[PDB]
Image: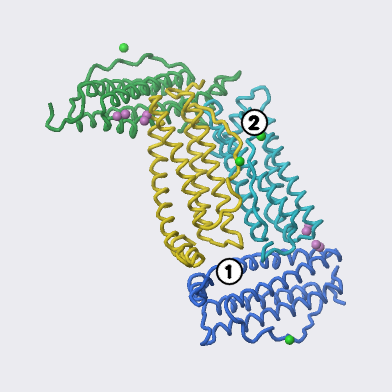
Chain colours: A green, B cyan, C yellow, D blue
Amino acid sequence: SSQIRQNYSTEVEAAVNRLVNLYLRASYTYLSLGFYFDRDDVALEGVCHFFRELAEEKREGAERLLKMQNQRGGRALFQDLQKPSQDEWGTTLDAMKAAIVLEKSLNQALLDLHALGSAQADPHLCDFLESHFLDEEVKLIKKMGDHLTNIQRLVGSQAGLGEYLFERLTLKH
Amino acid sequence: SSQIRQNYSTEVEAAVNRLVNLYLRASYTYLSLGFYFDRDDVALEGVCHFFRELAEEKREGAERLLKMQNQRGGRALFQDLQKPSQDEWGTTLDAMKAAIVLEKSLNQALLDLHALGSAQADPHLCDFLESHFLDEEVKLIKKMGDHLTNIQRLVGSQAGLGEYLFERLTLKH
Amino acid sequence: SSQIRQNYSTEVEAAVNRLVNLYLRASYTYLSLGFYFDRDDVALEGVCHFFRELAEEKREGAERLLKMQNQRGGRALFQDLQKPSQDEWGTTLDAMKAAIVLEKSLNQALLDLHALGSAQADPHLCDFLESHFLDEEVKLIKKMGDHLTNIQRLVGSQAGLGEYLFERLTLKH
Amino acid sequence: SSQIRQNYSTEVEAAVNRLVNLYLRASYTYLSLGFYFDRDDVALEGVCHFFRELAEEKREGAERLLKMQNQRGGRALFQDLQKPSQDEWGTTLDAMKAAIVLEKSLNQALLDLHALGSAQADPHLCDFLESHFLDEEVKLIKKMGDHLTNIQRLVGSQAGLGEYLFERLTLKH
Ligand SMILES: [Au+]
Ligand SMILES: [Au+]
Ligand SMILES: [Au+]
Ligand SMILES: [Au+]
Ligand SMILES: [Au+]
Ligand SMILES: [Au+]
Ligand SMILES: [Au+]
Ligand SMILES: [Au+]
Ligand SMILES: [Cl-]
Ligand SMILES: [Cl-]
Ligand SMILES: [Cl-]
Ligand SMILES: [Cl-]
């Protein structure tokens, strides 16, 4: 074991590596979501940009986890990254629903890792998650819920119109 | 009685304290309106900001009344503040209707206080209301009436769409 | 329940609403304290400003709690706001003693809410309180204790003089 | 009568001339107060400056009244100006008490003139007083009441000390 490793359980080390895998999986999902909305037959630029920005954010979360793994003396271990759950993502509504599902799973993984840290008496892990992840996730899930509400209200009887208007007047382009 | 008190009736002093209570009540109503429109399942940011800004304005009106009470040698007396009339505020249309009702009640209270001042020959009170409150209220009620008209025109057959469009293109975000 | 709500107990949701009520109550107390020290027959400008600034700070705490309630998918519920415990606040010493009592009650409410969060395994709630409230309160209570000490030392045999000097040379005007 | 005079009673015209006399009398009182506090055996610079600034303010009030008299087509008529009520003004407390008495008499004269204007249906006179005099007077009398309170609290058992401290730490020099 590391010359620097102190109070860092094998259990947390392994759960960190698994979380890295989740975040990179999530990043890959968002890359696929982003490019789907760039297809000439979908063509919702603001939706594409919203998902591409999330791909970067999730990559950044993984890189923060990997940096922390090294700072504690754990050993990064990478696994295969499973492709995203879908090749085509339907409407903006369908996509935002899938994104909120994905975020809830990340959030629950964070909470599970926090509980493990608390059981292992690892306050540096708890702090790290509280400072860099738990609020970021709460804020993002709230944003998504606000978006889902506005998208749903816009469906009405003219779905196409509502999807265009949401892209143009809420999402950034 | 105060070493400074001059031409300031007990009646006006008491009516000032009651008006302070009304303004603070109104402020609290607007705080509740503002946060309702911030719920993930309402999510009309511009509507939230319109009501939150009014919460501040009504607080400011109360503070101006309290400052004036002290300048005339009256004694501020605070009472309990009743909660707002509703916990949920319905649509933007429902909310704007409730706001205009509330403003009309404030306006009538101002006018009643002006009439009392006139009956008591208290020109400083009359001036104070004319200068800091009566036009502010007339302008606000007109703005609200303009908003109600535009919201109502937007309901048509596609209410959800109309509510989104009003938030996006009239209200500020 | 919310589409966004995750790991957020009904118990915490309700305790958050109660804390909002406490903070708004505290804000109202400070508004009354502030205006009392603005009376022509009290006239301690720096004491008035100290309490008015606290009224704003406590309002801000309530608004942060309400924002957080919405971000977690809870539902803000407002109750009646009880008036402050006194109509007249005595000397600067009396007022600062009442303020420290009030702050200790807020602090204890925060700690009680933190313990509930810990019992419910809600690390986002714990973080939120630790980051935005617990140190703010500790720092404020320390400031108050420092003020009480200086005010008490100034009473001596010339109370009036001491109260003037504290207002002029410690409090800001 | 003037080619311009319209709705301007002889009664208001005469009461305006009398008010001019009062304001100039008040100005002269403040000049005497100011120079008394400049005596080598009084030597309270900040008290001198407070009263000298008021001498100017009251002169300015008279000049505004005279300008208004001309704008309405009335004819300024000057009378003898009686000297101030005292040659020596005692302590800062004595002086501030005399000043508040003087201001109350000016205020009552303003209110009496407003009532006359109202009885004569002269809204321009009412406006003029409301806009340029009634609030200025209320604010000044409040300032004076605040000063009297602080001076009185400072007397205690060490009057000399209290008078020095009030001059140094409240009044400007
Ligand atoms: Au923990
Ligand atoms: Au921990
Ligand atoms: Au009036
Ligand atoms: Au009046
Ligand atoms: Au905790
Ligand atoms: Au916790
Ligand atoms: Au009038
Ligand atoms: Au009039
Ligand atoms: Cl797969
Ligand atoms: Cl009620
Ligand atoms: Cl009560
Ligand atoms: Cl004489």
* Ligand 12 neighbours mark 1 (CB distance < 8 Å): no
What kind of residue is marked 1? His
Q: Position of residue C161 (x, y in %)?
A: 49, 67
Secondary element under disc 1, as helix, strand or loop, is: helix
For mark 1, does the 10 Å Cα neighbourhood hold few (<14), some (14 to 19), or many (20 or more) residues? many
Q: Residue at x 41, y 28 (%)?
A: C117
Pointer 2 and pointer 1 on the same chain? no
For mark 2, does the 10 Å Cα neighbourhood hold few (<14), some (14 to 19), or many (20 or more) residues? few
Q: Position of residue A115 (x, y in %)?
A: 32, 23
Between D171 and C148, the one lying in front of the other is: C148
Secondary element under disc 2, as helix, strand or loop, is: loop
Answer whether labels 2 and 1 touch (C-beta < 8 Å): no
| Residue that mark 2 sits on | B86
Instruction: Tell me, for residue D147, which label it has, or none.
Output: 1
Between B87 and D74, the one lying in front of the other is: B87
For residue B30, what is the image quadrant?
top right
Image quadrant containing the N terminus of chain D:
bottom right
Q: Chain of mark 1?
A: D
What kind of residue is marked 2? Gln
Q: Residue at x 33, y 33 (%)?
A: A132
Instruction: Tell me, for residue B49, which label it has, or none.
Output: none
For residue A47, what is the image quadrant?
top left
Ligand 3's quadrant is bottom right
Q: Is residue D161 above or below residue B4?
A: below
Separation of residues labelled 2 and 1 (CA atoms) = 47 Å
Q: Is residue B171 above or below residue C162?
A: above
Q: Is residue B134 visible?
A: no
